[PDB]
Image (cartoon, coloured by chain):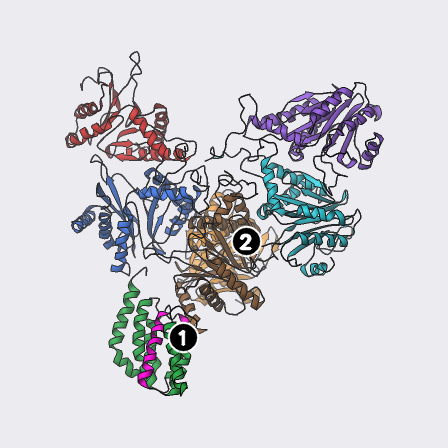
Amino acid sequence: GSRRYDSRTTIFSPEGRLYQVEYALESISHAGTAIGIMASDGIVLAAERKVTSTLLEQDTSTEKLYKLNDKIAVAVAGLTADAEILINTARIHAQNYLKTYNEDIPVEILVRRLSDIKQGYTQHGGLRPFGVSFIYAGYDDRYGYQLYTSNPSGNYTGWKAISVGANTSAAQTLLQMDYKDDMKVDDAIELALKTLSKTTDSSALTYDRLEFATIRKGANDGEVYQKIFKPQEIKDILVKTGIT
Amino acid sequence: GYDRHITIFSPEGRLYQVEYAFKATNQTNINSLAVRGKDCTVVISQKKVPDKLLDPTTVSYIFCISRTIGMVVNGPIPDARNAALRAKAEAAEFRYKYGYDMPCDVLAKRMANLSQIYTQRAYMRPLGVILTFVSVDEELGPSIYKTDPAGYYVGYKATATGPKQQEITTNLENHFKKSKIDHINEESWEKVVEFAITHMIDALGTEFSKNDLEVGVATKDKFFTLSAENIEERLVAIAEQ
Amino acid sequence: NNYDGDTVTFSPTGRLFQVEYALEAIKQGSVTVGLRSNTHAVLVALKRNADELSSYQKKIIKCDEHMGLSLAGLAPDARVLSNYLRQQCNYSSLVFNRKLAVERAGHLLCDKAQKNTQSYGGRPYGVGLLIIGYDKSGAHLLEFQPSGNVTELYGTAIGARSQGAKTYLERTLDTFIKIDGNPDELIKAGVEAISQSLRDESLTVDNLSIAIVGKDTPFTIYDGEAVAKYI
Amino acid sequence: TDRYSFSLTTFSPSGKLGQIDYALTAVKQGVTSLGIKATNGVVIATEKKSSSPLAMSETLSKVSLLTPDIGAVYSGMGPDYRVLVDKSRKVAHTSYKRIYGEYPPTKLLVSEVAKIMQEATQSGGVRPFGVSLLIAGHDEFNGFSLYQVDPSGSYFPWKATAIGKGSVAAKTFLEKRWNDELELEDAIHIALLTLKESVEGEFNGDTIELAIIGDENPDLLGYTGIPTDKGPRFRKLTSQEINDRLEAL
Amino acid sequence: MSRDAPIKADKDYSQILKEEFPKIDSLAQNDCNSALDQLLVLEKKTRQASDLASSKEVLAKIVDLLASRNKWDDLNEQLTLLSKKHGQLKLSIQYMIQKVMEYLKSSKSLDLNTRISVIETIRVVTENKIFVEVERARVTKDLVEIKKE
Amino acid sequence: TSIMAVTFKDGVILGADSRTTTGAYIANRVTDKLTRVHDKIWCCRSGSAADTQAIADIVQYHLELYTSQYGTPSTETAASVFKELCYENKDNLTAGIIVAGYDDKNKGEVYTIPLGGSVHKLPYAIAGSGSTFIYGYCDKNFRENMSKEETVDFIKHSLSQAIKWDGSSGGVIRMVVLTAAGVERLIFYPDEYEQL
Amino acid sequence: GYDLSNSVFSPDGRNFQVEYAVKAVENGTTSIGIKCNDGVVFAVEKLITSKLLVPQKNVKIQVVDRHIGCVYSGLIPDGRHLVNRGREEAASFKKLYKTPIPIPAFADRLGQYVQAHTLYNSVRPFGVSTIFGGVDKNGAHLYMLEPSGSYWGYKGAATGKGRQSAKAELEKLVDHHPEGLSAREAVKQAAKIIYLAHEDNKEKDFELEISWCSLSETNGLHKFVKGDLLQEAIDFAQKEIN
C-alpha cells in the first residue's frame, strides 16, 4: 500500500502541537550558537560554527553568514544544509521587490515570507519543515534597524538582543543583565564575544571558530555598510577584547 | 523493522529490499556464460524445457535489443521482458536523436540509472533480473557489460550467471591467466563457440544437448542466434578436437 | 488488518475479502426479483419506508424506455451506476443511432467497477443490480454481482431471502417462458416469487412496485392503486 | 496514483534528522578517497574495487570530470554517484553555460550541487543519496579550492580531508604530514601514502586512480595557437605513470 | 522428447538394419566405411536409449574389421570420433568398449594388433571415473598378460 | 528532383538523381537520396529536402524497434509509417516518398506516398517534379517481369529524359538493386547516358 | 511482513502476492488449448450453478483482432478488463502499420501490461490466466499467460481446477501423434479432455464451449464452434466417459 507506510507525521498532537516542529527545536539546540544584538548605531551578528575539525578550513568558510541583500544579512543556527534553500528563496524575494518597486525590501516583509514557507510545509503536502532558526539583521526606512528571530514553525518575534543555537538559556540571561539601550557598535562588538565565550562548545573561543559581521551606520551619509570581517581582522578584534 | 520492506536505509546504511532482488535469479536454474572471442562475442546459456507440453523453440532467454547487441537474461521471465522493452525503446531513442546506434556502454549505463530509480521510490519493486549485454562495437571492440538490480554495472572480460556460477568463473579466470590476454585467441568464431561449451560442461558437470543450450553470436555489425541444428554441429566438433 | 484494511492485497484464497463484505450489504438490504419471458421483462421490487410517517422508497430507476435497473443494496453506490448507465445509453443513441444492448451495457459496467477496486483507496460497490431491457435480441435479464460479473438468466433474485425466490422461479421456469404476449401473467407470478422472500415485511398496494418493458410497451413503472390489478 | 509526496526524511524523537545519518553511514561502508590541497594544485585519489576479477577497471570511473578545471570524486555508494554526477553536470550547463557562458567558479558550483542534495531530503518518493563528494577545483578568483559536499546538503572547505571507511585514520595521518606550503609533487606522495593505509587489498598503480587538478596542459583542450585560452587543469595520470609514483612515496 | 517421432523413427531404422545385418557384413570386406556410414547416422540422434541399442549393431559389424588386418586401423579412429562428439552421453561407447574385450580373447588376434587397439581405448576412459573403473582395470590387464611373457 | 522505382523479375531496382536545388542555386549535386531504413527495404526521397529527411529518420527509429521485438518489417508495413506521418502533416509538409523493397514474404514491391499521405501499390512508381514529364514514356515502354539488364537500362533511359527536361534533376544517376543475389549499387556518369 | 504489498520482497527470493494470484485461477474454470499444425483449438468448461442460466450466452471467449482467440479463467471481471486493454492494442497496431497485429506481438504486449501492476502498490494485479493463440505468417502459435506476467511456447496448455486432468491427457496425445495433429480432429479431442477435467468438477454440472482458429478450415480467422460440429463433439465425449 501507500497508507501502509505512513504513520502520519505532520498532524497535531493532543496538546495542539506539531510533532515535527517540537523535534526540530531540539535539533537546533545541537547546532552552534548564534547571537544577535542591536546597537543604536548598528546590528552585530556573531556566529559559532557547529563543526570544527582537524584540518577544516574555516579561514574562508562563509557557511553561517550570508548576505540576502546589501542591507539584510542573516546568521544561521541549525542545519546549514536545511538553511540553504530558504537563503536563496530570500535572495529572490528581495530582488523581486527591488525589481518592481525600485526600492529595497523591508525587513518585516522578507521575514514574514520565509515564515510562511515553513508554515506551508506542515499545512500541506505531508512534508517536513526545515530545522532552522534565523537571526535577521536588516535595515529599512520605516522601523530603522529591525532585529528578528524566526523558528521552524513559522513565526517571527522582535527582540533587542537574542540568542539561538546551543546554550540559549545561559546566553539569554547574561545578555539581559549586561545590555543597555545606549550601547554602540563598539560596546556590542565586545558584548557578543563575551557571551559566545560562555557558550563555546570547546573550552576556548578561537578566531577561526568565529564568524563575525556587522552592519554599521558609520558609513557616510547614514548609509549602512555590511562588513563580513576577514580572518585576520577577527583575530585582530578578539585579542582586543581580551579573550585570547 | 520497516526499512527492509521499502527501500529506505538501515542503521548500517544498507537497503535490504534491494539485496533480496539478487536472490531470485537462482530460482529459474538458468546459467549463462559469455566470453569475448577474437572477432566475436559468444554467449551460451541453458534452456530448461521440463515437459513435452512446452514447445522448446519458443523458450527464449535471448532478446535482441539492437541489430548488433544481444541480451541474455538470468532470472524471472516477467521482469526479463519488461527490462528488454525499456532497453529496446532507449536504443531506438538514441538512434533517432544522435544518428547512430546506441553504444553498448551507454545502454548499460542507462539501465543502471533506471534500476536506481526503481529503488529510489518506496512502492516500486526492483527488477530482479540480471542482464548480460553482449556486443562487438566499433569503438570499444568486443564488449560484455552485466547490469544488476541495484543499478551497478561494470565492464567485463567474461562473465557467468546462475546459481552455480562460481564454478564457471573459476574456470574462466584460470584460462585468462595462462593466456595472459583478456579475450580468447582462435580465428574462427565457430571454435570459440566450441571452447565455450567445453568450459561450461566442466563447470556444471553436465554435458548439454542442442535443446539444453541456446547460443547467441555477435560478430561485427551483427547479432544473430544459432538454431538447434547448428548447435548439434558444434557437439560433433567436440569429438573432433 | 492484513488483507481487510487494504483493497490492493491478495489473499492465497484467490479473493479480495472486501467483495464478500460488499456482498453482505445485500443480506441486510432490500430485495428485488426479476423474471422474463421471451417478449417482456418484469421487475417486482419490495419498497420500504423509513418509518410509518415516511413515504416508501422507490427502488427502480428508469434508465431509458428500453432499459431499467433496480438496486437491492446501498443507495449511494447505486447513484454512481445509474448515472453511468444513462450516460452510455444516451451515447449509443447519439453516436450509433441505436438502442444500447442489454448484454453490452452489463459488460461496460463490469469493467468500470473493476478499475475502481483496483485503485488503492477505492471501494467495491456494494449494490447488486438487476438490469432488464428489451433490445433486438428480445428480452434480457442480467444479474450484477458486487464482483461486477454479469450473468444471464430467465429469472433471478437478489437481496435478503433471494434463495427461496430462485426455488420458486425454477419450478415455474417452463411455465412463464411459454406464456408470450401477455405481460400480466408474469407479474402475477413475480408477486408469488417475492412472497417466498417475506419475513413479515408484507406486500401491500404501496409496498409493491412493478416495472415492465415490452416490444410494444415502453419502460413503465406501475405504482399506487394500479399495482392492485395484479393483487 | 501518487501518494508518495510525504518526505522520507524525518526527525528522530531525540533530535537529529535520522535519514541523512543513515546515508552518512553508507560512506563508512564505502571506498576511501582523499584530497590534499596544495598551494599550487590539488590532488584527488581513490581506489578501484570491483566485484569480479574479470571486471575492467579501464572503463570504471570513480574520478570524473565536471568542467575542464574542476574534478569530483566520491566515497559511498556507486549507483548513487553515477546518477548524481550527471545532475551536477546538468545544472552547471543549464545555469552557467547558457546564462553566464563560462565555466563556473568552484565556490559557485559547490553551492549549486548541495541544493540537489537538499531537494532529495524534501519531497516524497525520494530519500537522499548516500555518498560524500570531494570537489577539487581552481578558479582564477578564489584561487585553489578543495570542498567537501555532505549527504546532508552542506559544504565545507578543507585544508586536507578524506572520506570513506578509513576517513578517521586518514585525517590523523594528514595532521603531521600537512604544512601550509606544499608542492604538487609532494602532495601526490602524501595522498597515495595515506590511501595505502586505507586499502586492505594490494595497492597497485593499475588499481589506484590518480588525478591532479594541478598544472594546466594545453594539448588536452583540443586546439593550440591561442595561449590566452588553455586546456584542462584536470589531468588524469595513466597507469604506468602512477607506478613511477609508487616508488616516489 | 517434446514429440515422440525421433524415439520411434530411429527404432524403425534399427530393426531394419539389424535384419539387413548380413548384407552389411559382406559389404565391409569391399570397403568398411561405405557400409559403416549408414550406421553412424543412427548415433547422430540425441536419444541416448536408442543410440545404446544401435551400438549393438555396430559391435557385430566391426568384428570383420578385426579379422581384417588392414581395416582395424580405422576402427581406432572411429572410436575417437564418437567419444569426443558425445559418446551418446557416455553410454553408447561404454557398451562398445566393454564388449570388445571379450571378442579379442576368442579371435586370438596378433599381439601387435590387439595391443594398439586396447592402447587407444585406455586413453578414452581416463577422463571418467564415476563407474568406468569396473571395466577399466580389465582393459589395462589385457596389455599386461602378454607383456608378462 | 525525380525518383522512380520499377519492379522486375527477381526483385526491385530503385533509381534517383543526386542533384538538389533550392531556387536557381544548386546546393549540392552529389547528395545521395537513396536511404536505408532497413537492410532490405530502402526508400527514395524527393521534393523538399528537410521534410523527407525528417520523416525518414522517424521511420527508421520505429522500424528498428519493430525488428528487435516482432521480427522484420515487410515493404507494406514500412510504407504505412511514412504514410501516416504525412497524414498528420498533410497541410504542412510536401514530401514525395517512394518505398520499395525486396522481401521473401512478398517479392519486390513498390509503394508510393503523396504529399497528403496515401499509400498506393503500383508495378512502377514515379514521383517528384521532373518525373511527370517522363510519365508517358514510362507506361508506353514498360514491360512486366523484365531481365535485370533490361531494368537497369530502362531506369537509365527514363532518367536521361528526366534530366533532359528538368534542370533540377542532374548529376549522377544512382541505383540500388534489391535481390536474393546481393545488393548492388550502381552509378552512371553523365557521358555514359549521353551517348544514348 | 512481506504480505502487505507487491513491492516487498522476501529473503527467500519470492514474491507471495504474485504467487498467490496464481491460486485465484486455480479456483477458476477448466480451460485447455491444443497447439495444432494448422491452428489452435480452445475449449472451456462453463460451470452451471443453477438451471436459470441461459447456456452459451455467458461469454468467456472474446475475440481480439479478427484472428486471435482469447479465453480466460479465474476472477472474471479482471479477465474481461485484461481483454479490454488488448483490443486497444490491436487497433493501435493496425492504425500505424496497417496490418493486423501478429500472434507473437500480442503475446509480448500483454506480458508488459501484467508486469506493470505488480511493480506498484497503487494498482492491483490481475487474477486470471489467459489462453490465446492463432495463425500468422510465422505459423500457428499458442500461449498461456500467468498473472505473474510469464508466458512460454506451449505444445498444449491448461489451467483451472482440472489442469492436472487435462495435461495428463495431452502428454499421451503427443504420443499418439508425435508429428502434431490436425485442427479438425482436435475439436473432438478438445471436448474429450474437458470431460476428463470435469471429474474434478463432478459435484457440479457443466456446459461445454469450443472455439477454433485454423488455417485449413476457417481461412485463418477465429470463429466459434456451433451447430452440427458441436453436437458431434458433445456426443463423442459422452460415450467415452460412459
Q: Residue furthest front?
A: E148
Taking D144 as reference, is C163 left or right? Answer: left
The colour with which the image depicts chain F is orange
Q: Position of residue B138 (x, y in %)?
A: 57, 60
Chain drawn in blue: G
Q: Is residue F177 above or below residue A37?
A: below
Chain drawn in red: C
User: Badge 1 is on which residue?
Assistant: E81
Q: Chain of mark 1?
A: E
Taking E90 as reference, is D11 left or right? Answer: right
Chain drawn in green: E
Residue sitting at x 82%, y 35%: A235
Where disc 1 sits, the SS reads helix
Q: What is the three-letter code of the residue carrying label 2?
A: Met
Residue A144 is inside the magenta segment: no
User: Badge 2 is on which residue?
Assistant: B102
Chain drawn in purple: A
Among the 4 quarters of the image, the one containing residue G124: top left
What secondary structure characterizes most of the magenta part? helix
Chain drawn in cyan: D
State the extent of the magenta-drawn residues as a range.
E84-108
Crowd rating for badge 1 (residues with CA inside 10 Å; few <14, some 14–19, many 20+): some
Q: Number of labelled discs? A: 2
Q: Position of residue G189 (x, y in %)?
A: 23, 52
The CA distance from mark 2 to mark 1 is: 45 Å
Q: Position of residue D157 (x, y in %)?
A: 72, 41
Q: Position of residue B185 (x, y in %)?
A: 54, 68
Is residue F82 visible to the viewer in this orientation of the structure? no
